Amino acid sequence: MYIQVLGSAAGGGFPQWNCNCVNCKGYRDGTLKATARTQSSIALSDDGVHWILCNASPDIRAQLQAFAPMQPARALRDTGINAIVLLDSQIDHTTGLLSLREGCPHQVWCTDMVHQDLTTGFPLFNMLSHWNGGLQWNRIELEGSFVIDACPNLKFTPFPLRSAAPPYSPHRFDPHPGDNLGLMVEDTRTGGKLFYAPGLGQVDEKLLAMMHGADCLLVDGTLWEDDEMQRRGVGTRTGREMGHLAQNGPGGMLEVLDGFPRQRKVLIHINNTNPILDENSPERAEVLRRGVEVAFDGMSIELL
Amino acid sequence: MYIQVLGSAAGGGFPQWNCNCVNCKGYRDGTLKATARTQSSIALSDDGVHWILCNASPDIRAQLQAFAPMQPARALRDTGINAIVLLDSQIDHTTGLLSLREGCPHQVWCTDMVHQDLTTGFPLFNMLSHWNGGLQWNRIELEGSFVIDACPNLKFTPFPLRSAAPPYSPHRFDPHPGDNLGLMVEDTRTGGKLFYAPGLGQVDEKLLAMMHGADCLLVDGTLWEDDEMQRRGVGTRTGREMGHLAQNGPGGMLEVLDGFPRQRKVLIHINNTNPILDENSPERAEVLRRGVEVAFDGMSIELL
Ligand SMILES: [Zn+2]
Ligand SMILES: [Zn+2]
Image (tube, chains in turn green, brown):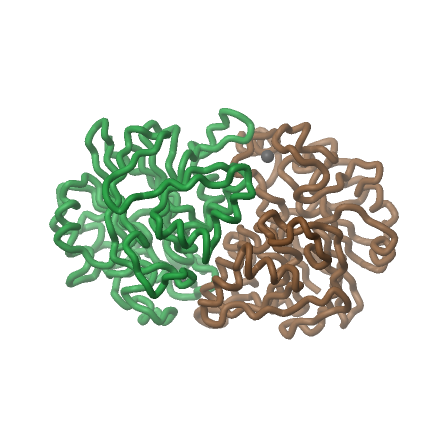
């Protein structure tokens, strides 16, 4: 199984178009060691030639250009994508599709709740249907596992992730399971298991239980402190909107990860406010020492 | 008046995500002198501090980063944009807005027909309304001129451009005037007049007439030959879909521009297939000799 990190930032990526905070005002000022990041998004494959896109970010164009396998040039008008999985119906996880319209049809994998939002509040499916077949919806049942034709060696098993639909959803006040869910990918050939959850509110008994059975833990590292938005003074919300659950602890990520030493633990979906975006920073050190790698654009994780 | 070229490509920009043609397969192969281009889009201003965005492309993020004035950093959470103008409701001219949601409200200028599409087929307005005020629609009457508060020295006078609404429009088969229109910007302080039309099917008597009264002609240079899609073998349509009217002539652009020597003539909205994308190319020479500059990302045109 080949895991490619196309995007590693969050929300407005990094630096954010309209944010002049420490990390952003800093990065632009050349007075801060850090690397720009596009909206979180990873690709998956078993043969390294056929890839399944996980969440289509608004930085889809640049992200594809930066990865050669996304363009095998095995023929004029050809792509390295064979299917896309949607973990929710957020704008920053589905806007990319609009940019893939010139290459339809695409096999989109998403629950019924998400497919509902994508045919109503944000009619990506309706819109694109006017583009050579459009998108072929593939339901992601709330129970069980699925497998895509392009990569028959990858076994997907999505787990429920207590969350709420985007503000444009016809049921934003009526949270149904299937709105936002994590992913458990297993390489049926070797047995390897990747635990992907760029969106985590708080772990429980059922989560941790299945986490230990994973070789690689790709959890979200949005904010260092539950109220990063408060210190930086750029946001109102806290530990709830756009990747929650800080890492500082207690009850934090860095803490819960401690019970997972025999496995690769990486932090993806980093917000522009997170201090772990500063190479030579104190909070960065704590993450490295704890044995947790901070995801970055271009990163290539593999299990085999 | 300060004219900034944020995007100069067309449709899938350049190189196109899924296109392996001569210019694209070439550019990636380092065996072709050319520069990457983002989706067509230009910015305008009279004071160089307040800018009015013309069409919000899907490459809005990268485009803003590449232009310092788009981020005056005069305060945390601040942008250099004060208003956006929409010349139509196409996906590649309005998707950018979704990425500007974290900084609402925005003043969006567009006709009633476009505003209709943006509240139905592609509900950008509905969707964004859930983001601090959202977007404040400013009607662009089919007759007359308008002026935005941020730049009181710029006078906009849009002219009708016989075209059709996008395939997701509830009236895609019922073409109404106001669907797609060009723009005539005048610097009321100096008198200067910029003629912007990244989408031109064919000029007439009323067009040419008003064109001579413009100091700068920023016309579209999508395809060199009416059937670029045919030679390259990547598209079906011809001289009608995504910037039409070749430049080779006769009846072409390079031809009609001849009657406009006393003024700056630039070609923007270039398609990936256009051979004028090859620095050292024969078709490129013909354009330069004819006195027509080929727009590029980062280009800064000024009249004063
Ligand atoms: Zn920031
Ligand atoms: Zn091409």
